[PDB]
Image (cartoon, rainbow over all chains, first blue to last red; front, side):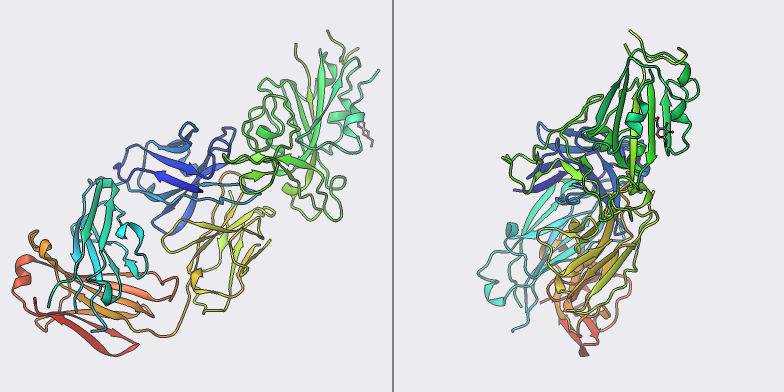
Length: 218
Length: 193
Length: 209
Ligand SMILES: *[C@@H]1O[C@H](CO)[C@@H](O)[C@H](O)[C@H]1NC(C)=O
C-alpha cells in the first residue's frame, strides 16, 4: 500500500509559477517529516526543502525566497509552490519521508520533471518500428518523434511486457524538439499471436497514445 | 535569604530534555553575582535584561528550568528558534524576559562506555506550546494503521536516546542548560535589598 | 554548510568483486549519514542509514562505517547505480557528489536489426530508418549508415542506454532521418557496425521491399 505519487507540472517558461503535488499512500503527510529532493539533468541529488511534522519550514539557500511547501491532510497531499521560477531549477523533483535517526527517507516518490524554457509545448508522433526478418529477426518497437519537453514514458501492453524493453534515452533533434525509440525483443513465435501496444504519454502535451506494432512483410 | 541558585546549577544530575525539570524560585534575595562570574559557560543569552544589572533588579516570580542537550542544539534554546528541540522538547515563549545559561559537560554526562540515559523527542504530530513538557511514550503512528502498542513500520518510539560518548564531537557532547524565567504578571526575588 | 566529497565515479569492478565508496565531509556529524542507490533511471532507494544500520530489504552485501565509507561485499549485476551519501547537518541536508558503479564483463556482440520507415510516417513528409544494436559490451561500437553503397554523415543520430541490471550490456540505436523525397531516390538502406566481438562488420540491408 506504500506509495508516494507525484502530480507535477512539466513546462512553465522562465519567470513563471508552478505547484507540485505528492499524493501519499502507506504514509501520512501531516504527521511525518516530508522533504523534497531534486536531481538536475546532471545526475546529482540536491536537497530542496522540508516541512517537519509540527509545521516548521526549512529550505535550501538556492530556493529560499522563491519556493514554499504546503500540505493538505484532507487529501493527504504535499505541495511545493515554485514561484519566481528560474532556469537552473530544471530538474526531476522527488518527495520523500525523512525519518532521520530511525531510517532516512525510507519511502520515495517516482519523479516529476520540471522544465523551464521560453519555448512552447509540442506533442509527439508515435510511429511504429515494425517486426520483420530465421532465428534472428528485427524486433518490435515504436518511435516517439518530435516532442517537447521531456520526458516521455513508453510502456507495452499497459504493463505486462517489461523484459527486453530498452527505452533509449532522448536525443535533441535539429529542430530543437526531442525524439527517442523504445524497442522490445520478444520471441518470433509470439509476434503473430501476441498483442503489442506501446503506451506513450507526454503529459506536458496531455498526449496519451497507444500504437499497435504488427509484423509486416518482405 | 539567598535564592538557591547553586541547588540548580551545581546539582548532581540533570533531567532529560523532553522531561525538563523546572524549579520555582521565589521568596528569596536574588544573587546573580555568582552566575556571570564563572567563565565556565559556553552560552549566556539574556533577553530583556543585560547580564550586568541583573543583581540589582526586583522580580515578581522566577522559574529555573534545566535539562541536557548536545552542543549543536544549544542554539535552538532561544525565543523563536525552531527545530526538533525547540518544537518537540523545550519551547520558550516569544516574550521571554530571562536568561539562557549553558555550559559544556562532557565530564559529568558522558559515561566511559557511552551514556544512553538522556533522551529527546524525535517524532511529535505538532509543535509544543510555550513551556510544555511532553512525558508521553505512546508509540508514534507515522501512518494510518493503528499501532496498538506494537512496534514496526509507521510505528516508532517517539523518544530517541542521546548517543553521549566521550569520543563524540564538540556538537555531540552534552551541554547542561539552565533557563531563568525572570519576570511576568507580588514580589520577592529582589537584588538591592 | 557541509561539503561531502565522495570517491571518483570511474569504478569498473567485475562481478563478485567489491566496491569501497568513501564519503568525507567538511564538518563531521556523528552517526548522521545515509547511503542511497539511484538505479539507472529510477528514484533513489535507501540502503544505509545512521552510518551503518541496514534497511529491511538491502542484501547482506551492503555495509557502512562511521570520514565515512560504503562497501559492497560481493558485487552483483543488480548493483549498477550512482551511490550518494546524505547527512543531517543543519538544513541543508547536503548530498554527495555521486559515485557511479560500473560492472565490467567479457566481450559481447550486438544483435543488429534494421527497421524501415513507417508507412504512416511518410504522409508527414519525413522518412527515418532505425538501426538497433542490442546487448553488447563494451560501448565502443561504430554504426555506419550506407545508402546506395555510399555513406551518411549528418542525418545520423545515436543514443545508447545504461548497462542492464541482468547482463550488464549496453544497447544503442542509430537513426538516419531524411525527407520523403530524398528517401525515394535511393533503393538500398543499410547500417554497418564494427565491434571487437564481431570479427567482421555485419551489414543489414533493405531495399524498400
Ligand atoms: C557552584 O559551586 C561553586 C564552587 O565550585 C560556587 O563558586 C558557585 O557559586 C556555585 N554555583 C552557584 C550557582 O552558586
